[PDB]
Every structure is written in C-alpha cells, then in structure tokens.
Image (cartoon, rainbow, N blue to C red):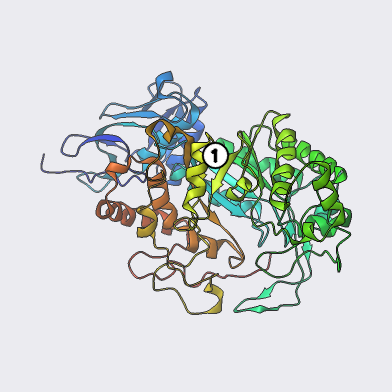
Amino acid sequence: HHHHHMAPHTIPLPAAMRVQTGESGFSLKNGVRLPEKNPLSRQAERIFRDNGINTALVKNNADIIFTEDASLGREGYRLAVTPDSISIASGSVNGTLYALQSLVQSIAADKNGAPALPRMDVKDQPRFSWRGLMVDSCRHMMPVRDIKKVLDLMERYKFNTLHWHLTDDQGWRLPIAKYPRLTTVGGARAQSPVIGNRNKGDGIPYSGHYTADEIRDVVRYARDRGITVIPEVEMPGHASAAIAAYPELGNTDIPGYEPRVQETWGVHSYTFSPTEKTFRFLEDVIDEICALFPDSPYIHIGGDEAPKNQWKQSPTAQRVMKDNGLANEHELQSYFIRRVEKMINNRGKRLIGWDEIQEGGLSPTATMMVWRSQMPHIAAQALAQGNDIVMTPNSHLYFDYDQGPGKPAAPEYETINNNQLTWQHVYGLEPVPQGTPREREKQVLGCQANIWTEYIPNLPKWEYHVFPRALALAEVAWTPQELKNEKDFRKRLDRQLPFLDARGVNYKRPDNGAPAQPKAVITRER
C-alpha cells in the first residue's frame, strides 16, 4: 500500500517471521476479544493489558483462536495474524505465552495512529532449553513483590529459568522447618560493608528470609509465567550462615573455630564438615527443598569456592579421608558432592553445581554450571565425559560487573570491579564452546546470567545491572546464531524503551549510559 506498518520489535528475534507491512492488518483500536472458556485467555488478558490493549472475555467470535499442535513441543509456537483473526498455535501453555509476548511486541500504528498488528506469520522455537537469570537473595534480599516484577520481565523476553541463590556466607534465606535457626540466626548479620567504603563495616544489622508460603508463591507465580524456579543451597563452601546457626555442622576441631554470619564480601573459609551428622542434616534440608520446589528438575548444591584449609586442619576430616581412601581434600570434596547427589537422585531430581564440582572427579551424572571463563578446558572436559552443562561465563554473563560509560559517580552506583561488560559484549556471546562435537551440542543446555548482589541493595540498582544486558542475553539464548545482527538488535532495543519507561524500569540507557530513573532510591532499607 502506501501505509506500511513498522516491523515487530520482538526480542528475542523469532526464528522465522514473515511480515507483509503493506497489507491490511488487525486493528486493536477497540481491544481484543478473548474466548471466555479457554484458560489461556487469562494469560492473554494479562499480557495485552501490560501493553496498553483492552481485552474482553467473550462467549463467541473471539479475535484470538488458540490451537494445539504437539509438534511445537514445550516452547514452540506459530502466529498467524490477518484482519479477521489472530491464530496462536502451541504444544504447551508456555509456547502460547511466548506467542503472546511476540504479538504485543508486534503492535504498530495504523494509518490513523491507532494500535494494530500487521499481517504476519511466525514460526518460532528456542535454540536453548535453559534460558536463565540467577537472583542472589543472600548478599541483599529482595522482597517477593520485587521478584514478581523481575519474573514479569523475564517472561516478556522468554526467559524460562530462575536460579534462586538462597544460602551463602552473609545470610541464609531458605525456610527449613526442622532447623529453624538457619533463618532465625543464619538470616541475620550484624552489619554490612559501608556503601562506597567496602573495607569498613556499617554497624547496621541486616536480616531476613522468605517464609515457606512466600517460597511457594514465587514458584507458582513463576510457573504461571513459564518459568521454572531452581533452588540453590551452597555446599560445602559458602556455608558460614548455616554453620553460625548450628556450629556442629562446621569443622569444630580446627584452631580458632569462630563461625559467624559473615559481614564482609569475598570468599570465606568456613566449610561444612564431611561427617555422618552433616550428611544427615543435608539430607533433611534436601528433603524440605523437594517439598518446597516439587516440580524443579534440579537442585543446585553450589560447589564453588570451597577453600580446603579447614579440612586440612581438621583431624575429623582427615580421618574421614582415610576411612574412604581419599588421597587429598579435592577428593574429599568430590566425595561430599557424590553423597549429596545420591540424596537428590533418590528424590527424583538431578544435581547441578558450579564447575568446581569436577575437583577430585566429576560425577558422570551431575550437570555443570560453567562460570570460570579463565579455565576453558573445564567445560570441554565436562562435555567430553558426557555431562550436561549450563553456560554462565564470567567473561560475558556476570551482571554484577560494570557496564560502559555513563553511570553516576555516586557511591550508590559502585560495583564489584571496573570491568566493562556492555550489552554489545553480551550480544556477541556464543554459548557452545568452540570445537564441541556436533553430536554433543545437545549437552549445552543453554545459558544464564548471574546477578550477585554484594553491591546491589535493591530493585532500581538491580534493574540498572540487568537491563538492557538481559535483552541481549535473551536473544543469544533463543535466536539462531546466524540471525544475530547487532545493528538490527539496537533498533529493536530502542523500540522496547517506551514499555520499560511505562513500568519505571531503571535500565542503563543505551544512548548515554545514564540511569533511566536517575532519582530512583538505592538503599538497604526494607
């Protein structure tokens, strides 16, 4: 025609999309009619209204037709938009969610400036099955209402996994009924590093945990948005809060044994003891995790950054090594993780751990979360041994890292280091390691960014660290590698900003690097 609709601004870019911008589209000026009997209409209602489009549940002659096609699998979908109807095909609920998110990101102005959808056809499915973000609730804790805002944005960009880092040295947030001190004692630290002066303590206690009903509410809310919540309980390291709560779980026979919920960032030395009592405790904890996260295919057990010195100094640990023919403390760690894997497997789930779990021997059935990009042989060795991996490289996907220029100099915006990890860097990530045999590519489950919160006290700063980098990651995680194009991505990114502004998201502006919400308050108060 003479009027051409704008092309969709969907991120991630769909694998196959045919838009006839000149043809007559579907008018949204009077809202969308949804079939009142289909449960998917309630999700369409939510997503359309999130984007300023009115909806009505109707008895007959709805505007949207939902169809079932098992060949689209867990997450694939088709879209067909004509002036007469919007047809959405999926093999599961989550494919319909993704179709709906693509639809609202295809809304364009008609001749008269009213919202419309162009004549278009989409067939789409993700490259990777694991498309994740990790929330660190230990260093700072975010309330449920803020996690829910995160999960809404994760669904918009087709993330399907929330890795919930729930226990560490500076706080334990996971409610365990049988061991209430884990949260009443382990959920509280006496102070935190001063903002802008990290080598000094602020003298202000910081405490909290999620109640069991809050855990279950987050899991359900996520599930309704296509997202599986995977819990992490850290062991054998990053354990100071649990050991402070129950000092018998640590290496009590070492010189100068003084556990506490830690008040400082970095690596700490308090590790779980490798005793029968500790394994009984861990089995009880794993049992309650399975009750809180009954649909999670995995339990993440950490496994990262566990210093061996306390085990070296502990006669108890040395005797366990001799009992079990273990030559060194790396083999002791492998033994520890093997015993916990049995607990997880006996409850029908799979173990995942940080790539340090290959120390002393990588279990043939574990899944490895690869983060140490300075050691590229670890992922290669894990793949060659047949193990599944999830790529969370600190070269590309550690979103505690700084970004490009433009941030405020104020101490509130300080970060762990001065590495600049830009959204452009993220967009250039290719998750499959070079040289991976074609037949082993299916072992690369996907990728995920980790948002460590030492320097991220609350949601406005979290948003600054995560958006727009998470949009680049969403495309890496979903879109075929050969369709990535940074120039086109930037055009689609710019057209996302009005939606993000309407929610007041404090993203890092692509144009000048400044916060989108420069007056947002960044504070530890809750």
Mark yes or no: residue 69 visible.
Answer: no
Helix, strand or loop for disc 1: loop
The image position of residue 496, as x and y in percent, is 36, 53
Q: Is residue 191 above or below residue 378?
A: below
* Residue drawn at (54%, 39%) of the image: 227
Horizontally, is 39 left or right of 299 in the view?
left
Task: For the C terminus, give its image quadrant.
Answer: bottom right
Instruction: Report whether 445 appears left or right of 16.
Output: right
> Which quadrant would residue 19 be assigned to in this image?
top left
In percent of width and height, residue 288 lies at 77, 38
Q: Is residue 185 above or below residue 57?
A: below
The picture places residue 440, in percent across and down from the top left corner, at 44, 33
Q: Name the residue located 78 percent from the left edge and 59 percent from the top edge.
A: 312
- Pick the front one: 330 or 89: 330
Q: Nearer the viewer, residue 286 or 218?
A: 286
How would you rate the neighbour count of disc 1 (Cα within 10 Å): few for under 14, some for 14-19, many for 20 or more? many
User: Does residue 446 appear in the picture of this structure?
Assistant: yes
Which sits in the foreground, 429 or 202? 429
Image height of 349 relative to 311, above or below:
above
- The residue at 66%/50% (across/down) is 303
**Residue 486 image-quadrant placement:** bottom left
**Residue 114 appears in which quarter of the rendering?**
top left
Q: Nearer the viewer, residue 92 or 247?
A: 247
Q: Residue at x 78, y 36 (%)?
A: 287
Q: Is 254 left, or right, of 416 in this rendering?
A: right
Q: Which residue is mark 1?
A: 227
Q: Where 504 sits versus 108, above or below?
A: below
